[PDB]
Length: 98
Image (cartoon, rainbow, N blue to C red; front, side):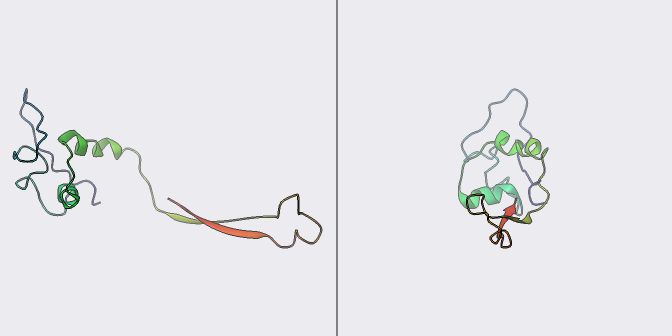
């Protein structure tokens, strides 16, 4: 829910795409910076991105990631050391999906 706040402007038709952050037409200008938006989080890092750079968020949104979950897997010991008494004890290791 913090990701939908893109503050790219409505560029007038048949106009050049601004690149420097000194003009107000740039999305990283202080005039077009509302708090709790992606532009202030980019400016806190002081990185330079364009209008289409933040416009790629709306098509990056097409694939979603639900939530991270914990996976604990286990298996028997390997066939090089699998005997009648080692098969009782298994190996237990865990991982983090997403």
